[PDB]
Length: 173
Ligand SMILES: [Zn+2]
Ligand SMILES: [Zn+2]
Image (cartoon, rainbow, N blue to C red; front, side, top):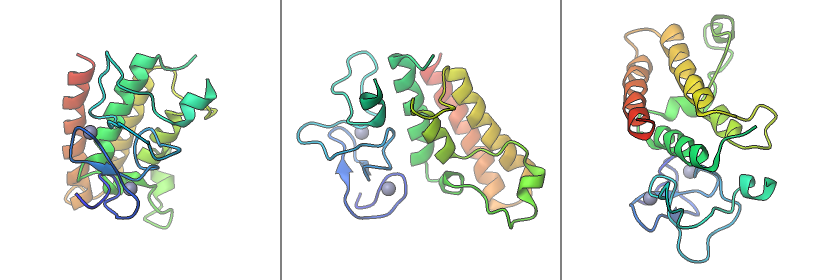
């Protein structure tokens, strides 16, 4: 591809060595703070057991938090969501000008918040994978609560939440 696997825009893109996906440094999960000089494998391709390489990311410079194992598994789940063609409406928060969204939705959630909370520096960083899964489910519950049932965004949410459940059972059997 010539466009970022996450945001579908061009520019300065990093290619994975093992799959066709390319990424902006800030769109990969975790975000990268430099362009790698040699081998580089994306979070979806990286091995859980034998990490080919550590990433130049914020959590690597920072060091009750995710174990290294759970960190990789949760980054895989979140990057899988961000790369899915149905996920784009969930990358950013709904405008407060849309139908009193923030009256209806008392606990808003989107993928940019989930990305941020995977970073240990965040005051509200995840300490368990259950918290990550809870935020993803909250996000899709909010989508179903707010959006018109017949709308394209509601249908996308219904499909993507079920794709996620499938990935979850692969990654946390
Ligand atoms: Zn991007
Ligand atoms: Zn890859």
